[PDB]
Image (cartoon, rainbow, N blue to C red; front, side, top):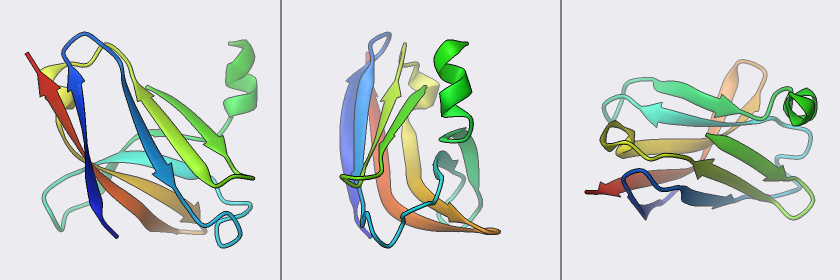
Length: 106
């Protein structure tokens, strides 16, 4: 997979897009996670679980028919900068859809 850079500004929002194969990943929840070192774990930030309930009650929206996962980081902080993955989850595994480098300007 590739890595694309999304450049944001401290205290503002930042939209990240991760297109994917809508047939290969049909029925799978997605995750946005922070990569810890290049070979360490990817630490969860948000996932698509319970999005329906959370309607009533970082934002994440998944267009499963079109194959696009959108993550919106809000009130960007310098510590939000760094490398992340968009992931597709199945069983105990996670397929990496994309790597994303978040840059935060201040």
